[PDB]
Amino acid sequence: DHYNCVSAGGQCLYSACPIFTKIQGTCYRGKAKCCK
Image (tube, rainbow, N blue to C red):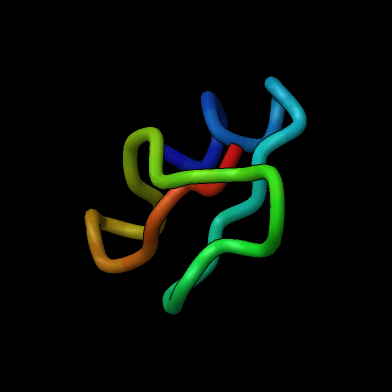
């Protein structure tokens, strides 16, 4: 979720992750990815 994602330094993104991150969980009622 957004809380776990961002509190760890991840981003909640609806599309592909930026360099040096990958999908690890979700955000926003499961509709976005957590990229970290």
